[PDB]
Image (tube, rainbow over all chains, first blue to last red; front, top):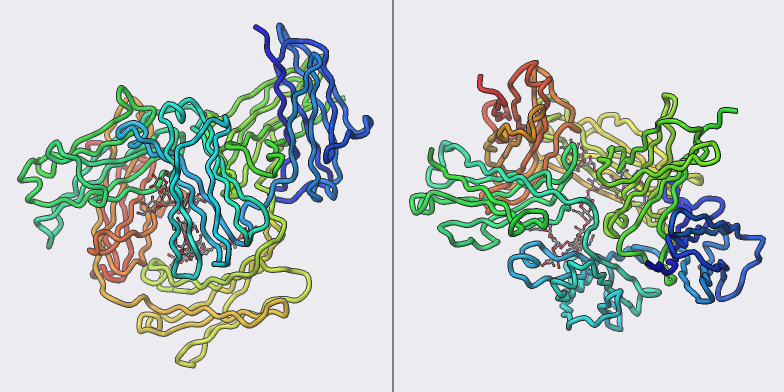
Length: 319
Length: 320
Ligand SMILES: *[C@@H]1O[C@H](CO)[C@@H](O[C@@H]2O[C@H](CO)[C@@H](O[C@@H]3O[C@H](CO[C@H]4O[C@H](CO[C@@H]5O[C@H](CO)[C@@H](O)[C@H](O)[C@@H]5O)[C@@H](O)[C@H](O[C@H]5O[C@H](CO)[C@@H](O)[C@H](O)[C@@H]5O)[C@@H]4O)[C@@H](O)[C@H](O[C@H]4O[C@H](CO)[C@@H](O)[C@H](O)[C@@H]4O)[C@@H]3O)[C@H](O)[C@H]2NC(C)=O)[C@H](O)[C@H]1NC(C)=O
Ligand SMILES: *[C@@H]1O[C@H](CO)[C@@H](O[C@@H]2O[C@H](CO)[C@@H](O[C@@H]3O[C@H](CO[C@H]4O[C@H](CO[C@H]5O[C@H](CO)[C@@H](O)[C@H](O)[C@@H]5O)[C@@H](O)[C@H](O[C@H]5O[C@H](CO)[C@@H](O)[C@H](O)[C@@H]5O)[C@@H]4O)[C@@H](O)[C@H](O[C@H]4O[C@H](CO)[C@@H](O)[C@H](O)[C@@H]4O)[C@@H]3O)[C@H](O)[C@H]2NC(C)=O)[C@H](O)[C@H]1NC(C)=O
């Protein structure tokens, strides 16, 4: 029934063109907590700021109370990389949160990408995985460090790096940390921190399960009519659509045996003209295969599908 | 008196280290708006986003109303620099506010791209042009000199130029040049050359008819079945494959109208299995549309298609 105070900071957003506002407001929120003596103080690089600079108010609703504090900063100050801490003292105890201008996302043309677990792995193979790919940089001296960490601080299995210099003259490091199935589904957060000796500071990407509403995919499989010239081959295509989140896995099975991934392609999830995503899968098939057993199954693994997180539709070439 | 609403968008703050949260929450605050119904709407790049990913809250306590709507995004999504908008509707005209990832400290440099005649312009309109686009230009001081030329040395037509200031303060200069069909078709190579005092050495991009083998595209138009979940709209799909080279234009024709590009979602050419390239197109049609004329044709334009660089298939949502 007791609800400790929780601290979080919101900030003025950027221009529709990513431009900073003349002034930056930092709104500190201490939402839904068991009413009690509370105080909110702001720190700029570890020091207490003038009371005249932040306006604080608290209100209650029912069994819990909520309070907020707004601080205005000169754009010049916000851009100087000074750190600002919202310090809350609830019932004599201290709760804190900090922020500073967001660092460059693409330092020196460089890019970083951390991805979530594919649905097949998470549900079918039951061996979840997250891959951290860092690209768009040039070879220097010192090596590149990719460490994995969990928000919960809880340990993390042993990852695996594997860079591979590219043609355009850049390097591409890629590590793949394995995650705890349960761990991931519970909403854990896995961050991928990378310190490049050539690059200024540390670049960091964080990943966790989607939160939005779920919606199972609709699966429709079609077989191309015979096309003049190519009589022993046929193409299968299935549209899997109107599903959420966008994360999905597509597999094809023939003769109760699932075929190898290289046997077909699948587009990237793209939104529908309404709610949800759609994907197209294509399987080039052969006469030997359909005269074998004339049924091919387009299977989709999505977290919203039930009972076993999968939905499928079979198709046959002949009528 | 009657107090006019005001939209403001706050966002998740970064780490104490300047790192982003595993997910970014955007909070839209339309405050002061005098009590009364109101419709908040989010837009991801102009596209209206289904309200299945939002939440309206309101407390017109004391007097004037104040409602807020929050939208959440994954780090990736946010990092893709997609621009988000929050639309309020009150007394007719809608009010709004937009936001995007803040521009990194050091802004990039100029990059030039040279497109190629689209199969459509080349074979349907028979009026092909190649475009030269210079992006991320530092305006104010100086101006970019973009000049065309042919490898044959022959004369080039007059091109038209366009200069557009982007919301991120960068500049875009678009020179688009009419080219001869016979000339393009026969291998003429065109070069675009960019210059500017705030530019080290001159830039140069060239373009010429794609080389290699040719293969005519195959076209298949399908229709998803009618079911209780989609009864006043239907999803059409089309698969165009095994064509070479990659260049191809895809449209959906209906009732003698060439639907807007925006109407459909068409993928970019991927290698089949060496057999050539393939593309997938998906179009959502409405009852009104098929009741006007129950026939939608998927057309692909490709140089290798006989006899008029065109191949097409029609599909119907209803038993004729
Ligand atoms: C400030 O804000 C600026 C925007 O407001 C932003 O500028 C953007 O910069 C980037 C790079 O810096 C630019 O990206 C490049 O865009 C090129 C042009 O794309 C468009 O034209 C293409 C060519 O024209 C077609 O030609 C074919 C035949 O060849 C015809 O069939 C067709 O009809 C056209 O004539 C075209 O292919 C593109 O099509 C896309 O859009 C249509 C829309 O419906 C869609 O249907 C298609 O499926 C497709 O998505 C465009 O119309 C492009 O050629 C470049 O491609 C290179 O780079 C990309 C990287 O994404 C890579 O994938 C490619 O393989 C290739 O190497 C590239 O995408 C962008 O155009 C600029 N936007 C502008 C000027 O409006 C600034 O960057 C920003 N500043 C910052 C960083 O803060
Ligand atoms: C110089 O050359 C290098 C050569 O590598 C080149 O590097 C590429 O750089 C681009 C960016 O410019 C990279 O593209 C980005 O890739 C991001 C991640 O994509 C990869 O991972 C996807 C997920 O699978 C991974 O993770 C799971 C989970 O752990 C794991 O199970 C998997 O094993 C795997 O590790 C994967 O889907 C994706 O594969 C693509 O291609 C296949 C082709 O078969 C296709 O089927 C897939 O659907 C997919 O398209 C890939 O392996 C990605 O998140 C990121 O997203 C942004 O860009 C896209 C553009 O399409 C936007 O749509 C989106 O909104 C985001 O903004 C982006 O796609 C690319 O991956 C690098 N290449 C490498 C090494 O993979 C440099 O660009 C060159 N430099 C110069 C000169 O410019």
